[PDB]
Amino acid sequence: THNQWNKPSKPKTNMKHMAGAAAAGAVVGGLGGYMLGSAMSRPMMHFGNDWEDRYYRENMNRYPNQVYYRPVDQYNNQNNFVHDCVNITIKQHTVTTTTNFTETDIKIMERVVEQMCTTQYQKESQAYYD
Amino acid sequence: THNQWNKPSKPKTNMKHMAGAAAAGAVVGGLGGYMLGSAMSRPMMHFGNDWEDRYYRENMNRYPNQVYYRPVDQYNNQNNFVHDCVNITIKQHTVTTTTNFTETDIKIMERVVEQMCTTQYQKESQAYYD
Amino acid sequence: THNQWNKPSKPKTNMKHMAGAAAAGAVVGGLGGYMLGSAMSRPMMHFGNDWEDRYYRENMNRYPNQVYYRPVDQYNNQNNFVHDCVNITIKQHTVTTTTNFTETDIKIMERVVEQMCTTQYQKESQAYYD
């Protein structure tokens, strides 16, 4: 004879996002790829009594992994920025009190802020006078 | 004879998003890809009594993985920005008190803010006088 | 005869994101790749009684791993920035009090902030006078 009792008392299980793809305030975006943040799983579990006599299983499988990885990548620009440019403060004040002459004031690119947490492949900059 | 009892008391299970694709305030967007944040799973579970005598299963499968990965990627621009440019403060004040002459004031790009958390492949900039 | 009792008292399990891909405020983005932050797992577990007599399993598998890794990568620009440019303070003040002459003031690129946490492959910069 066989007897199998199973009397759990108030069991609690949390299988949220089990064997799945979860993304929370993230980026799963690439220029290239074949498997980015995916799930291909075959998990097995038991939580009670189990009993097996004479089985055959999981024998003579043939699943070799064969890959030819030949990409060409040239003159690209990729950047991954996380938590950059935090708590930046810039202050630039000016105070002037003034009181038969000739004055001239010529200025270029005065009090300029540029390129805070930017990415580029190429740039040029010409700032001159004649 | 065979007997199988199963008397759980108030069991709690959370299988939200199990073996699925979940995205919460995220981006799953790429230029290229074959599997981005997907789920291809075959999970098995039992939560009570189990009993099996003489079965044959999961034998002589043939599922080899064969891939030819040959992309061409040239002169692209990709960027992944997460939590950038937080808590930025810029302050630029000016105070002037003034009291037979010739004055001249020529300024270019005065008090300019530029390119805060931008991306680019190329740029040029000409700021000059004649 | 066979007897199997299973009487757990208030068991608690946390299988959140088990055998899956999870991303929380991260980037899983690359220029190239074949498996980036993926899951290919076959975990087995039991949490109660178990009993097995005469089984055959997991025999004569053939799953060799064969890869030809031949990529070409030329003139690329990639950068991974995490927690850069934190708590930056810049202060540049100016105070002037003034009271038959000829004045001339010529300035270029005066009080400039540039290139805070930027990436580049190439740049040029010309700042001159004539």
Image: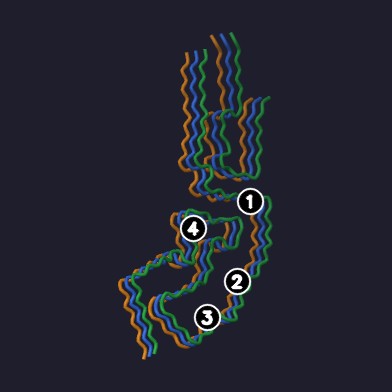
Chain colours: A blue, B orange, C green
Q: Return the chain for callout 1.
A: A
Q: Which kind of residue does numbered mark 2 sit on? A: Asn
Which numbered circle lies on residue C107?
Answer: none
Residue C14: horizontal and vertical position, in percent? Answer: 41, 65
Q: Nearer the viewer, mark 2 or mark 3?
A: 3
Q: Which kind of residue does numbered mark 3 sit on? A: Glu
Residue A50: horizontal and vertical position, in percent? Answer: 42, 81
Residue B39: horizontal and vertical position, in percent? Answer: 49, 66
Q: What whole-number distance in Å separates the C-alpha atoms at marks 1 and 3?
A: 46 Å
**Quadrant location of the C terminus of chain C?**
top right
Q: Are marks 2 and 4 in contact (CB under 8 Å)?
A: no
Q: Which kind of residue does numbered mark 4 sit on? A: Ala
Q: Nearer the viewer, residue B110 or B95?
A: B95
- For the point 56% across and 13% down, the residue is B102
Residue B42: horizontal and vertical position, in percent? Answer: 48, 73
Q: Nearer the viewer, mark 2 or mark 4?
A: 4
Which numbered circle lies on residue A76?
Answer: 1
**On the image, numbered disc 2 is attached to which residue?**
B65
Q: What whole-number distance in Å separates the C-alpha atoms at marks 2 and 4?
A: 26 Å
Q: Are marks 4 and 3 in contact (CB under 8 Å)?
A: no
**On the image, numbered disc 3 is attached to which residue?**
B58
Q: Nearer the viewer, mark 1 or mark 3?
A: 3
- For the point 49% across and 74% down, the residue is C44
| Label 1 element class | loop
**On the image, numbered disc 4 is attached to which residue?**
C23
Q: Nearer the viewer, residue C83 or A80?
A: C83
